[PDB]
Length: 21
Image (cartoon, rainbow, N blue to C red; front, side, top):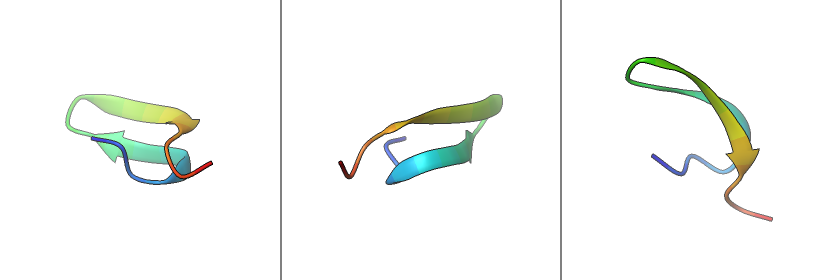
């Protein structure tokens, strides 16, 4: 869901964001 910063594959698509920043 919130896998750190960068881009991760959350289920349906690559979700890039700033989780751990």
